[PDB]
Image (cartoon, rainbow, N blue to C red):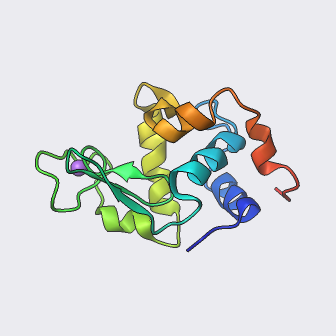
Amino acid sequence: KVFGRCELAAAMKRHGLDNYRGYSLGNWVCAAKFESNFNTQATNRNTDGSTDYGILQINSRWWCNDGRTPGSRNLCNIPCSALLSSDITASVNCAKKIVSDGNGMNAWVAWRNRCKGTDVQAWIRGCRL
Ligand code: NA
């Protein structure tokens, strides 16, 4: 499913991401925009053999099991395919585990290079939250 900007914001807010670990909603919508362009079915393979899945492009090396990433840890205890669902619940639950990790949202390269330090509030403006 391809989410609308405000539709995703509301869905993320309802799942408790607004200000989770101090990161405002704008940060999460911005990350999803540049990671997958709001497409829950987005997949991208990396040179190390791992693959990123879903709206938040969660990596198979440490967070989910896709059956083809040797030495993966599956920290979110879930099949990577579950992260491609129209229901973002799984991606959100795993993201909360990731952001609590230790490096915060810096775990997401697009957020560091394209969202961090910018006016993230702009991503939820005009929305009925
Ligand atoms: Na894994």
Q: Residue shown at 26%/43% (left/top)?
A: 62
Q: Is residue 43 left or right of residue 89?
A: left
Q: Is residue 75 left or right of residue 89?
A: left
Residue 17 seen in this snapshot: no
Residue 4 seen in this snapshot: yes
Residue furthest out toward the left: 70
Q: Is residue 59 left or right of residue 28?
A: left
Q: Residue shown at 42%/25% (left/top)?
A: 102
Quarter the N terminus occupies: bottom right
Quarter the C terminus occupies: bottom right
Q: Residue shown at 15%/59% (left/top)?
A: 68
State whether residue 93 is above or below residue 83: above
Give the x, y percent position of residue 24: 69, 37
Q: Quadrant of residue 127?
A: bottom right
Q: Quadrant of residue 128?
A: bottom right
Total marks drawn?
A: 0
Give the x, y percent position of residue 64: 29, 54
Give the x, y percent position of residue 80: 31, 61
Give the x, y percent position of residue 60: 27, 51
